[PDB]
Structure formats: C-alpha cells, structure tokens
Image 1: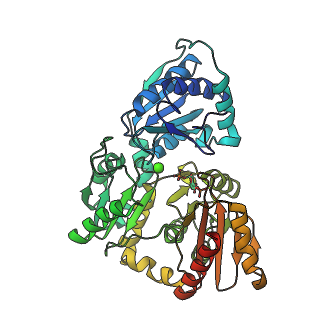
Image 2: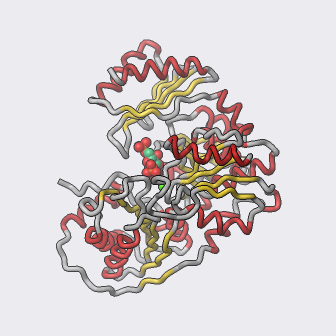
Length: 448
Ligand SMILES: O=P([O-])(O)O[C@H]1O[C@H](COP(=O)(O)O)[C@@H](O)[C@H](O)[C@H]1O
Ligand SMILES: [Ca+2]
C-alpha cells in the first residue's frame, strides 16, 4: 500500500505504527531534497511526543546538510511566520491538532511559508520516505535555538492602533494548548483585562484535548464569559491557528460571520483590497466585503487554494467559515492571534459589542452550520439531491463540489479533502423557516 499518515494537506497518524522517529528522520531527509537552498525552521506543539519527532526531523535535515532553526514550543503560525521572516527554505510544525493521545503529525511549508501538499511535494516526500532504506548519515549542518519572539509579537501588534484600544475584559481559553504563552507575551502591550481559563500548557490535557467546537469544551468559555461579565471570549485549538469567539452573552459565534466581520476590519486599513472567501457560505461575505469597499474573490475551500488565490490576487485577507483566517502581511498565512486583536480593536473603536457587530448579519443570512453525512455512496447521494431540485432550475457552480443558488436560498454540498464525508451548508435570505425546511429536506435525501 502507501503510508497512511501522508494526507492531502499534512502528515498525521498514530504513533508508532503510522508515524515514529524513524519515519520523521526519513521525512527530514526527503524534505531537504525538495526545498530550495536555505535553513529549515522547526517547531512543535504541547503533545508529549512532539519534541522527539522534531529532534528526528532535525537529525535527518542536518544529515542532509540543512541548517536547522529550532523555534521550540510554539504555535503553527510561528513556524509560518519565522519561515518567512528568516527567509528560510522551509519549515515544519510538529502538531497533533485534536487527534487522539497516541497520534501526532506535521505541517510542512517551503519558502515564504507556501504550503507543501499532496500534489505539491508531500506525496513526493512520501514516496521517497517509502523507498528509503539508506543508513542514517551523520550531521553535516548545525542547529540553532531561536527563542526570540520579538519580531513575531511586533508583527501581531502592528495590526491594531494600540492607542485606540479600550480596557476590555476578555476571557482567553488556551484549552491547555499553547496559546497562553503568546497571550501573556502580548498582555504587557495591551490594556485588556484577561480572564485566563485552562491557561497552562499541559500535553496531558487534564481538561480534554483542545477542541472548542465540542459542546462541553465550548461551554467552559461561555461560562467564564457570563460569570465574569466579559466583553467577549476567545478560545483556541491546541496549536492556536484556529480561534473561536464568544459574545458577551456567552453565545458562540458561528465562524461564517467572522469572515465578513474581519474583512470589514481589514478593509478599513487596506482600502479597495481583495478578500478571498470559500464557496460553502458566501452571501454575507460578498455583501460585507462590498459594503466596506473591497472586492470578494470566490475560491475553492482549503488553505492551499485560498493562499494561492490570495497571492495571485494580492488579496489582503482570506477567510474560511471553519475558523481559518489568512493575512497577506503575515506571509499569506493563517493566524489564530491576528483575528482577536482585530476584533478587540473593532469593539474598542466602534463602541459596539461583538454581539451587535454580528446580530443583524446573522438574521439577514442565517445558515445551517456545516452538517456532515457519512453515507454508503456519496456520488449517488449527491445525485439524489440534484435530481430532486432539478425542476427548480437553480444556478449551479462547481468551484468546490456543487453550489446551487435558488434565489432566496442556496446550498453547497462537498466531499471533504480531509475525511471521506459529505459536508452540507445551507443559507437563506433572512428566512429561518426556509432554512430549516430546506436543510431537513436535503438531509432526508442524503440519508436515503
Ligand atoms: O481542519 P484543519 O485545521 O486541518 O484545516 C484543513 O481542513 C479544513 C477542512 O477541509 P475539508 O472541509 O475538505 O474537510 C480546510 O477548510 C482547511 O483550509 C484545511 O487547512
Ligand atoms: Ca490547529
């Protein structure tokens, strides 16, 4: 067969049968052969086994004559930032995201933190690793420890006018991942009053593997917001490239609405800019981008397509409904830190609560949320949906699965690139009843 750990966008698998130190070293050797010349940035998340996988990557890279820049325990976005900032040949973040305790993984980038994906080098690496029976060579290059986060912290703070910030009370919930380190380094430079929840990094995860989308994890942030009268709450995944917002009522804000909100925030600083968005949920983003004087650019979902489209368009910002936010000035990469700084600035400057900033948009373009379906036959299931609606003559778009626009409602139906599932998103023009009846109708067809 083929090594299962090599996925479309990254490497992820159970340790040690799908990923281990020998494979990690071989990945380092193979990666050295794929990159242009220069050093390689390495960082890792809070999982207990991550440092040893990084050390194995480093051994293989250095056996292949690559200098290694070890940035230590960090967020994924720090690997992206430092790879670009230091003009490195590439970078690897060792991260397990929210996979089980016996799992780990890696995200790989080349120059300017450009993604390395299945069809842009990752399967080439896999094939090299798979055939590699060579004896491990000894190091012919050095490793440097780079602990300095100054340039990264200065870059994050450059997105806001600090003199306009108000002393908002913010709940912050690292979920025992790595986000609290950066919050604490930012805090001396900000006026906010932080309420720290699950703040200490702990790869044993006494409060569960970080995943703010799980209701029991979500509720911990909501409770802290309500009990402390916080202006809003922020939670992160473990490697903090995803962030999640809770308004002052404790309500979790569906990620779709953050795309339009962040776009308006960014367009106030970069007028007339292009904003890239995914095709799952669109109407609100298109309107909000245009209303702020920007130009919306539809793009297939997935960070590699988004980043490539942003580059070719000089787009200032790109956002996916699933809590991924990309910034041109940040090497076109995603950050879980930039978004909450921008939102804190917008609440501070506008005098409006986060709730008020989104309320009317949520009423105007209500959405189903992404609903996933494991079915026996995805192709036959999609066909059942399309045949059912053919007599309504929707406008069809195939940018990413099938998007069907009926006028007052639309849907997107996609096969995932990360799981063998069908994913449904429905939205309507201000009509909650139509949203529910159409969502349920499609659901019944998919399950038939
Ligand atoms: O989930 P992550 O953080 O690994 O993120 C990855 O998978 C997501 C879901 O993709 P799909 O809907 O095809 O399953 C993508 O939107 C995202 O751009 C990609 O980086
Ligand atoms: Ca993540």
